[PDB]
Image (cartoon, rainbow, N blue to C red):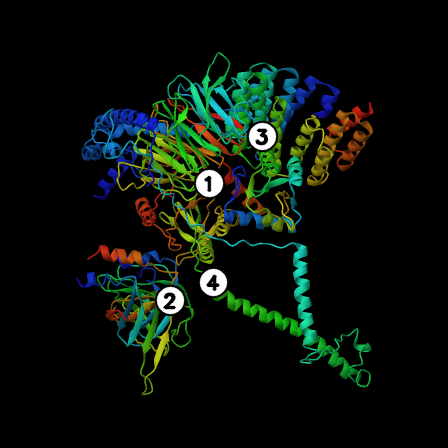
Amino acid sequence: LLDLSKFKIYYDNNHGYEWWDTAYLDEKGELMEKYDMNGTSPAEEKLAEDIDEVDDDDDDEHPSIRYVAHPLPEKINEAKVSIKAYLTQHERKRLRRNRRKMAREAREIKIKLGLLPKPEPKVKLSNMMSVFENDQNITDPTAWEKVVKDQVDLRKRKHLEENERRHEDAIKRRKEAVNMNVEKPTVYHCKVFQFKNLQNPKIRFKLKMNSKELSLKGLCLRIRDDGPGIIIVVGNEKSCKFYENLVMKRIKWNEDFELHTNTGDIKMDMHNNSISKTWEGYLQDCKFKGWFMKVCNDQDSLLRTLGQFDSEHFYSPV
Amino acid sequence: IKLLGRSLQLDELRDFFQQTFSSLEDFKISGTERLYYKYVNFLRYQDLNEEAIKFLNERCLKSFPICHKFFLQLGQIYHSMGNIEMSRETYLSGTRLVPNCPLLWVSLSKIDEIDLKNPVRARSILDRGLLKNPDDVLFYIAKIQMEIRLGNLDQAELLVTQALQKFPSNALLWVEQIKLFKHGNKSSLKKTIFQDALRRTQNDHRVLLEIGVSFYAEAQYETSLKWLERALKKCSRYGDTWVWLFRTYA
Amino acid sequence: FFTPATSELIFARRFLINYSLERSRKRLQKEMERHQKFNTRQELLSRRTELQRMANLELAGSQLVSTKPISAVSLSTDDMVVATGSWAGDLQVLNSQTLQPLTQKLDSHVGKIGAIDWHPDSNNQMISCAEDGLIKNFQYSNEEGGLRLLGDLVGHERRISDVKYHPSGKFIGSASHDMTWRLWDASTHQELLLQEGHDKGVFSLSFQCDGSLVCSGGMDSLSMLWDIRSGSKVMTLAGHSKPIYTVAWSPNGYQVATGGGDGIINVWDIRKRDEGQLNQILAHRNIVTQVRFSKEDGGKKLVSCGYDNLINVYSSDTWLKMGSLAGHTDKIISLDISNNSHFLVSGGWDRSIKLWN
Amino acid sequence: MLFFSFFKTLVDQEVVVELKNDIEIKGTLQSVDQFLNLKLDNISCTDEKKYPHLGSVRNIFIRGSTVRYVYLNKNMVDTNLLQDATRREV
Amino acid sequence: APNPKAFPLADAALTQQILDVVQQAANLRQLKKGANEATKTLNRGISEFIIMAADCEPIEILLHLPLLCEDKNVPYVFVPSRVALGRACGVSRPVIAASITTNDASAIKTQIYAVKDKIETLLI
Amino acid sequence: TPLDLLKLNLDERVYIKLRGARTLVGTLQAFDSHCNIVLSDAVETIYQLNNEELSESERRCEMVFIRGDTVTLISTP
Amino acid sequence: TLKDYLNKRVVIIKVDGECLIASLNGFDKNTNLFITNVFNRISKEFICKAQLLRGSEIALVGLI
């Protein structure tokens, strides 16, 4: 039976009357006939509602031939991106000068109509020898040195501490911030690629992790593991670009690699394998809920999978 | 071979070549080997008799080398003895076999434009060549040259600009641009352009030479001489510069 | 909603309906006949052959034209000469197969040429638009010289994108960066329509070859199929995301095909009342500039050029990249196909016209 | 056949497997069969006390009945496809 | 409302992007502001892409630049706001024309290229 | 029929009880003829009586496969 | 499958508790292991020269 099946398949191969490598052409007649019947007019859906009717010199009544329409022009909801107004160098300087000045003034007041802190003398190892406000400066030489060096360290340490604090707070913000930002995406750039092979782990890993990083809605489908396959990547433009770069410049799909298994570590020489960008467009809506890498046993299956997002077309048989 | 040529001893040269040939049979998978020698042999043959080459080309080039230079040589030979269509065919074949060689494409273009008077075909060919390999600036340069050769100068300029955008450093493009400028459409934005070229090409040997030539054309001769000297300093091994210098001196 | 009227339109509208209807009926009959006499094998084979031919087209002749780039390339009805508008405001014409000029006409338009169309009555009185902001009919003579203009037609305010001739020959539709698309009276050179149906300009038109339906492709991505007779629409904007820079029908009224800025050519309007796309096609990496078909005269074959430096061809049943056409060096802004044969003439930013054979 | 298929689809996967008798082992899944057995390559440590008394055992064969879970992450497993499959079946 | 002849006008996001690019170029000295400077750039060939102001009144004083670009095959937009453009450039005074110039070794080459591509897309 | 009935609460939160006093809460993403379950966004709660006093042990796992031998009850919380 | 495990020493752990080092010489579809040269893992106690281990008992098997 198996042999028979094989034979049949072979027969089909040589000359297919319709085959799904390239989606079938042939137009069915029965359907057309049915459509015609439905129409009942010898014309089409568009014209059918003039329905064999004639008034005066051919005219109609159900849809009027007198009036000119001026229908409602649907205004698209444009996303108000409040503009990054920039500053001149001079402007920036002025801003810096004034805020800082104000701060200084405050400090002065909050230390002269205030005495809320005190201002000490900023020693260093070059001052050291010349400061006398703090005592012991020759009296206790090494004590003095310790004090001054210590002070310096504190200053430096304080600076470093401040930096650390900043780092911490930024980190704290960022996690929260990402979570907060569930902004409504207006338009999605997409790029769909296809590759002859990817029996390498590394490439697959790259595809995964990068996608995860970049909120990259999409997938990577393929046939029979070793066989050819497609990537569809979608998101913000920059991310897409990055992905493309990774695909084309960073990765070498013509590299020789190793497969690690229980039986033995298999060398895979693939000079034949290559990669091409098919599409690089803008999709009206991104129906890809995440990045759903897959494999399929067959082409039909792959097609079906693709059409789970109501979009087969991304694939290109060659 | 060179020595022989200098001396001029035809039969002797032939004998030498024959001797070399016998030895040659051991040299399988040798670097810059027969491919070089065979070209030289062809040239020698051409220096006297044309047809006799062709058989060798048919035989030897086909087997081991499969190299563009041979095709070019063949084309040249054909040109020398008329047979234009045949030459064109040969060129086409070469292109089909080796897409990645601008020279062949250029030759084809020339044949299209100069020999028969249909530039459009030549242009098309050039375009095709360019498409086949956008790695090389050479194709672009060739195209520019072709454009220059015919009346159309704006187009040429545009092409040059495009080339620059794609590969800014390539001295030949700069040279072409300079040449275009020298035509005297602007006769201005000239010095600035030259400066720009110099900057981009890090005072490229050839750019300097081109500048000198332009100045020569304009007939400001001391300046031209200076430019030529500069070019020489940058790299004396290059030729046309010397010629230009000589001309200036004259 | 907001419905006044005019008398000229009324006079014409009835005629349009009659003409459209009869022709439509004929087309339907033809279609019926086709299904009745076709077979799985031979037709399929023929199609395959055609596809192969399309694929193995290569760039025959690239003839330069103009200072600025070549907005429009339009092959005559006769299919003998091609007309090539450049951005300068000049519309040279070339004997297609050799591709050598007849004349130049800079003093025609001052602005950027839009589209050129040829008149479908073989009597060659081509129309052309511009950003200039006026269309011009040109009685073309092979012998006399080149072109003589017949009439100018000031209707739009802003710059025009595209004119077409309604397959009758009695009307010329023109769409512009103004909000409207406007159908003209071929004889008297006076307007009738003005569909204020888009929030931004109508960037492209396309009549259906039966003569019933005109798709106005807008800069909004609102492709509106207007029954001209009715002033009533059977639309989907749900095709495109960026602007619809072109639209064109499979001559078999069966299909509309809108080419986009998004690049995705959307081919829709079908017997299917649900109006779903048999497919969307991924046309060009950058944007799509022109979309064409060619079943007048031969078989139906989608062909499009883009701002990607590639023309390409699609099977009108499958919708697939049947073959890329490397040939241009730079952007390709327009294109036409030889009615009878395999012989594309396309132009653009390379500032040349180019043939494919 | 759904579940088997799913298992197969997870070929070459570092996954933790908790058994009935307090044995938690990590490993790279290789072979999958009708009764849902797991052969794991490169056995690594998960916990200190629960992980059994092994060391040089780099390849194992887990009996399908004795597994409690097969501890996947949220980036290592199918879901609504499985649901669809279930729906299709009776 | 913006001028019809100022074409192609950008869109909002696109405009923003372009201004960002301009700013970057300004910091890196890879930009030139001003109609005349834009013209100069065009003449040279150094112009990667030209940015004009739609809200230039009287618009005419730009509307050679587009022509020049067309004849040199440099992409170009108008943005809407000349004030904004000026600010981007780094000039309090309101500016109409700027040119992001060419330089292979820019950090911002890639970014610039993106913007150029976008501009080209607009043109038709 | 019972299997069919469980097709309603797919892709929503569920409450699953196993043998050995192991409460599993997540969202139902899979089942079949033998009732093998795959939970996403899950969290395990292990009741374990030791030293004559009650003590729960929480194992947090963002996904988990469950074999049908262990399963007792499926419901919603 | 236990076809790679035949003619090789293997570490086999049961459901109840014990762990056995021995040479696997036969398997079937029900996981009944035919074993030779039997030994215990922890105790190092020689049970016998040959035995059969029922598939219900096998919790884990390991190649070594």
Residue found farthest to the bottom: F52
Q: Are marks 1 and 3 on the same chain?
A: no
Q: Are marks 3 and 4 on the same chain?
A: no
| Residue type marked 4 | Val
Which residue does the numbered mark 4 point to in the structure image? Answer: A178
Q: Quadrant of residue D80?
A: bottom left
Q: Which of marks 1 and 3 is in front?
A: 1
Which residue does the numbered mark 1 point to in the structure image? Answer: C285
Residue F50 visible? The answer is: yes
Q: Picture coordinates of residue B184 (x, y %)?
A: 70, 26
Chain letter for the residue marked with disc 4 in the picture: A
The one nearer the camera, B56 or F64, is F64
Instruction: Give the spatial CA distance, label 4 vs label 2.
Output: 20 Å
Q: Quadrant of residue B34?
A: top right
Q: In which quarter of the image is residue A86?
A: bottom right
Question: Where D85 falls versus B61 (above or below)?
Answer: below
| Residue type marked 2 | Glu
The answer to whether F21 appears left or right of A125 in the picture is left
| Residue type marked 3 | Pro
Chain letter for the residue marked with disc 1 in the picture: C
Q: Picture coordinates of residue C229 (x, y %)?
A: 30, 31
Q: How crowded is mark 1: few (under 14 residues within 10 Å), some or many (20 or more)?
A: many
